[PDB]
Length: 336
Ligand SMILES: Nc1nc2c(ncn2[C@@H]2O[C@H](COP(=O)(O)OP(=O)(O)OP(O)(O)=S)[C@@H](O)[C@H]2O)c(=O)[nH]1
Ligand SMILES: [Mg+2]
Image 1 (tube, rainbow, N blue to C red):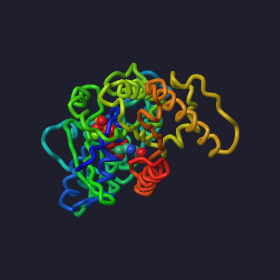
Image 2: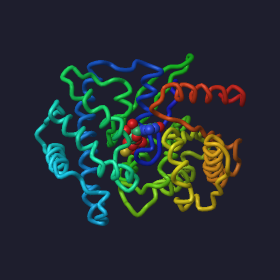
Image 3: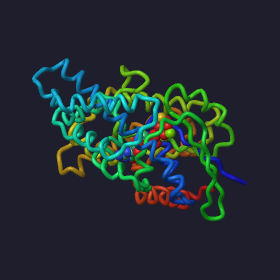
C-alpha cells in the first residue's frame, strides 16, 4: 500500500530539484557513477549560460551604446567561439582552455552588467554558481558533488518516479515537466493522488515565461495553481505548497519591489530591518496563495488541506526541516 505524491508547478519552479532532494534525504542517493553522468549536463548548462549572456549583452548594446554593455573585443570573440561549441552537435567537454575563456568572459564588466539583467534574459539559475566554479568543473578528475547535481538544470520532458520509505510508510513521488507543452501529460497522473506538492517560485515575480515573454512568471504560477485546484480529480486531495527559491527571494525583494508584478500591485512595503521586510513580503504572498485556495475549496479544511511552506530546494537542512514540519503539522492536526 503505497501513497502517491505528485510534483506539480510551472517550469523551473523547482520540482526536479525537490525530486533529487527526496532521493538524497530518504534513500541513497548518489551514486558516483550516476554523479559522473551529470558532467555533460553541467557543461551544457555552462555553455548555455555563456550563450545567453553573450547574445543578451549584444542586444543590450544595440539598445544602449553608453556603452555599459560593450564587451572587450577579446571577450566578444571568446564569447562567440564558446557559444558555437555549445550549439555544435559534436560533444566537446569543458577542458582547461575552455574554462579559462569562460572565466574571462564571466569577468568582463559588460557581461556582469548583462548578468544584472538576468530577469530579462532566460538565464539558468545555476549560472553564477557554475561560472564562478568553472575551473573546478574543468579538471580531468572532476566528479560532480551532490550540490552540483542539485544546481544542474535539465528541462524535464518525461515522467519519472521514485519510491521511498519513512516510518513504516511507503511513498511514490512523481516528477513531471511544468512548461506549457508538458502539461498535457499531467492529466493521466491525476488519479489516486494522496497529496500534490505544488512548487511555486517566490523569486519569479519580475520575470516572464520562457514559453511566452509577454507573460509574467508569477501570474502564470497563480493561474496554474487555480487551474489545478479547480480540477475535479483534486477536489478532496491535499496540497502542500512549496514556495520555493526562498533564498533568491530574500535578496530580490530587498532590491526589486513586489509591485513590479501585476498580482502584487497592491503591496505596501513596511519599514524596518531586512528581516521584517523579508518576513512581511513573504506573509503577503502566502495570504495570496491562501486566498486562491479558499476561493476554490467550498468546505475549506474539511474538504482538503492546503499548507504553505517557504523552501529552498537546493538546501538539505531547509528541506529536511520542511518535511519534518509536514509530519509535525499532521500529528497536531490528527490527520492520517
Ligand atoms: N537558488 C535556488 N535555485 C533553485 C532552487 N530550486 C531550484 N533551483 C534551480 O533552478 C533550476 C530549475 O529547477 P528545476 O528543478 O529543474 O525546475 P522544474 O520545476 O523541474 O522545471 P521543469 O522540469 O518543469 S522545466 C535548477 O537548476 C535548480 O538548481 C532554489 O530553491 N533556490
Ligand atoms: Mg523538472
